[PDB]
Length: 115
Length: 321
Image 1: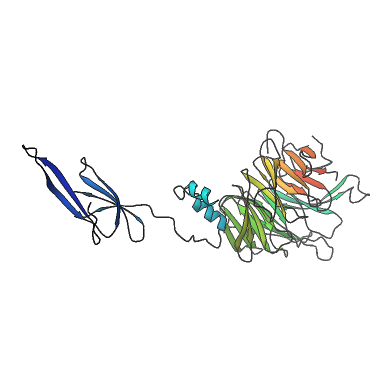
Image 2 (image 1 turned 180 degrees about the vertical axis):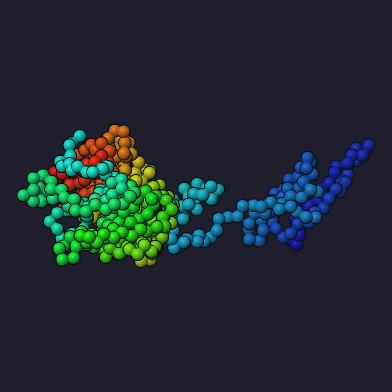
């Protein structure tokens, strides 16, 4: 992975050894990225994929993979919504408790830390 | 087990019993009880109110054919026995999921109106206006519904579980209490149609809740095996929680004369339904009565006396104050 200020680039190479113990890189592929910030990447020889993890301009989590120019998206889970709509018929307490204790809704460690 | 202080024979099984909590202008206390297919209205006079009565004077005033098993009875505040303009009004819920409003002059004019719209069994109902114009009902359809006397639905609150008990606030206008089977007690404002507040029980199922008329900050209920008391606005948590019955509590009712006395009933059980009368200052019941199979629990308006319906009998316990 080559980080540049305008655009990122991936390059995949094969290592070649000639009869004279001379090593060279053979060039397999080159893949451009958007203005997203790269956190990590790996690649598999079983599937021939590059797996890559980024943040966008709003700091949301972006994951994509590509067989080594289109990146396949991973549907990452959004964060919970900023505002909770409460009906005129709902007790505010019940609505907020249901949201907070909902499966995958929140992590104990955060609530225990706020208390 | 204390014997009942007084016992009155009835024609059939008593499924519900309610004293008139209002002043009817008569010397006797009005009592309603629901059978398999009828509602009886009676006058009760006790030796403790009039020294000319030996024990209990029980007089049937009127019998209404209902045709269905009555599950709850609510008195209208307009109920008067005054000779100038006698008016009997009460509401009933039955196994057919309908409310019936009965009106009578204690003479020949006997009218009833049927109200439909609950999709599940009605568990409880009350008059929810000082003027006696509005009825609140709760049931297994997970609704609390408000009705005029015309049978039009004025309001509907969606509950999170079956509504098990409903009570009008004794002093504060527009405040309805609704007890839900999952342990939540909600308060609704009938002017704003909004939930104001909730309480949560530590045990489930919550089966009955009542307001203390003498101290409107106190709520009592039965949930699981235990009786539970809250004092508002101090906490959403119970102030007291103690065992009421060895196997499932069913009804809770506050005494109308004493803010520290209440009665509980066990569930229609193999060990004959126990009535337990509690005093908050005591860790144990002050009185334990046995009724062979009994449903309904009500307190006399003035006397420290409670009634439970049973197999073809009403059982009365006087509590020494």
